[PDB]
Image (cartoon, coloured by chain):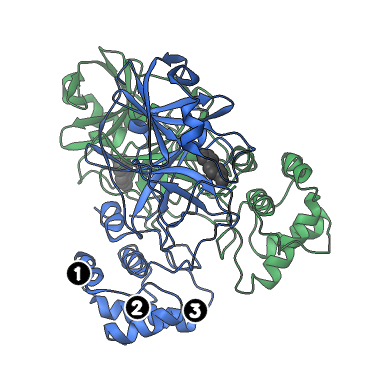
Chain colours: A green, B blue
Amino acid sequence: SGFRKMAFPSGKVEGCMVQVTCGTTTLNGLWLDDVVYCPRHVICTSEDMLNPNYEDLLIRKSNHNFLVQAGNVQLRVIGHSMQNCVLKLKVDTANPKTPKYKFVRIQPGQTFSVLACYNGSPSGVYQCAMRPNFTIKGSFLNGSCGSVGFNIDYDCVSFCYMHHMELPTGVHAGTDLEGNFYGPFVDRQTAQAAGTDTTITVNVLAWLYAAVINGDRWFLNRFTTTLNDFNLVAMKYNYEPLTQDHVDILGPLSAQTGIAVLDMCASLKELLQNGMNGRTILGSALLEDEFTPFDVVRQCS
Amino acid sequence: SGFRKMAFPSGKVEGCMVQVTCGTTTLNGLWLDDVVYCPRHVICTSEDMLNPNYEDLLIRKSNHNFLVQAGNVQLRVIGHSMQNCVLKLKVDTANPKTPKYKFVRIQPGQTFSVLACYNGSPSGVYQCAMRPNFTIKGSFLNGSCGSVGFNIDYDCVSFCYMHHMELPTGVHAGTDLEGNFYGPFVDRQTAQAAGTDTTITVNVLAWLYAAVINGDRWFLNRFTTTLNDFNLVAMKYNYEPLTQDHVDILGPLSAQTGIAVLDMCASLKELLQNGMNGRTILGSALLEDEFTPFDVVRQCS
Ligand SMILES: *c1nnc(-c2ccc(Cl)cc2)o1
Ligand SMILES: *c1nnc(-c2ccc(Cl)cc2)o1
């Protein structure tokens, strides 16, 4: 038994992490097939960051100005293009370690593993969730630029996130592997602020179900409630409004434990109105919102 | 910035995970050079688990009874021996992916990354700490047997843990890579119970220092205290007694933040006597004990 915050094995993504340098900017790149994907911040200097014209900054760049270094193997750039906020550097050698991959744009609430890299070398791996305000709460220092977020399902590596910025809030914002930012964030040192970070309600319910499977069952109540009356309490405590699609996905969890979803919603309603009274659920004194219903069934199979 | 529960990149360990089967038992093995390390539980049946004679159970086994399968590549067993509670199966092919490795026996308080495997295939990776009672709090289902714990320092993979059992407490017990269990645990379905799980005091202090670096500084108090008077409160709340070796290791952390170690001990003393008053430190409502002083400086460099 046991239940932990678990990240996918990062081996298949390590073999794709490289080091990209252009001018004075050096960051991490993603080497898939014969293309190296990196944030377009690589072509910018610390002065033109309040409002950079990335188009004009790229017209003065050419293939020989981009330095891609895989470990120590240096790749020959034979092309370059700017797709939204990422740069696609066509190299001469295809990565012999390129896995089965796809580019996914996840929805707010889904999770992914982040392989933090510095100058092309992997440093650590941790699990993150796309918050409702399209931000993430991770660990990114100077040089973590180009670090990717991914899910590995069976044999396909579904890349979904590439790290770009850290907001003044300490939270992090990034793009999909096609260059489009998650949320209303631009790659400029302008006045950017994330909205209300609500709580992913369906993920908390899945985490409560994982607690029943691992022993902690004290929060199980003798009440029940309706979907509208629970969304009443959910809105007052700034929780995501629960939908019927959310109830349907929690079906398998409600079937193994034999606890209806709405009976679990009443337990969450009591936990939001009365707190935990100094107790813990799965070793935490807070309500966990980074486990999707799939994350629980994966770790409980 | 940011600070997360981070695990080492598991790529170098994935290339060493294999599947071992003997008789009816199938578990995971560690393929380093031309030897496959696996728990000796592999030679046992579900009846002789109250008190198995592993010696006699092995005299009826031979090299052809052990089935090692790396992915689908099957290895030829040319030797076998029992070192304490692990089995060393000499194979014919050396692993082409064998990294720089060493066998380490860690001390209570140190951390390591666990690569959870099922039937030789990696499933997830998470960080664990060797609790003071020589147990760990991880996630191990049926088939996680032989899963290893490791630290990767620079280029050397320091294997330190191999998973064996789950106690009735839900906690987990295992051995070093030489077969010796951590603590007074035997590989028998006998009456086994872990002792008092105290709190690693020096790790909590390092985590409080990481909070000051990442913004959360409300717990910083205007008091101070002595080492003996803090150990007074530490013992009452079942904390590990703080030593001067502990104070010396936190030196670098006290130098960057400009906060003396004993001034931080007074803040922890107030947090143990008055709680958190509904607040959070680094996003947690509890006191975190799985970050060593090295884990903080690694994630803050
Ligand atoms: C790493 N990669 N991109 C960045 C970045 C982009 C825009 C701004 Cl305003 C700051 C940092 O950092
Ligand atoms: C996996 N590997 N070893 C074991 C085990 C050993 C002893 C006992 Cl009593 C239970 C399980 O599981």
Is the C-beta separation of discs 1 and 3 under 8 Å?
no
* Residue at 47 percent of width and 48 percent of height: A135
Give the percent coordinates (x, y) of residue B25: 56, 29
Q: Amino acid at mark 1?
A: Asp
* Residue at 71 percent of width and 63 percent of height: A219
Distance Cα–Cα, label 3 vs label 2? 14 Å
Helix, strand or loop under label 3: loop
Give the percent coordinates (x, y) of residue A60: 19, 26
Residue assigned mark 1: B248
Helix, strand or loop under label 1: helix
Q: Residues within 10 Å of mark 2 (few under 14, many from 20)?
A: some
Tags 1 and 2 on a common chain: yes
Between marks 1 and 3 in the image, the one whose residue lies nearer the viewer: 1
Decide if residue A166 is in sight here: yes
Give the letter of the chain under mark 3: B
Split into quadrants, the picture shows ligand 1 in the one at top left
- In the shown orientation, is residue A41 left or right of residue B118? left
**Near-viewer residue (A114 or B120):** B120
**Residue A237, located in which quarter of the rendered image?**
bottom right
Q: Residues within 10 Å of mark 3 (few under 14, many from 20)?
A: some
Q: Is mark 1 within 8 Å of ligand 1?
A: no
Is the C-beta separation of discs 1 and 2 under 8 Å?
no
Helix, strand or loop under label 2: loop
Disc number placed over residue B275 in the picture, else none = 3
Distance Cα–Cα, label 1 vs label 3? 27 Å
Residue assigned mark 2: B220
- In the shown orientation, is residue B154 left or right of residue A271? left
Q: Is mark 2 within 8 Å of ligand 1?
A: no
Distance Cα–Cα, label 1 vs label 2? 20 Å
Decide if residue A157 is in sight here: no
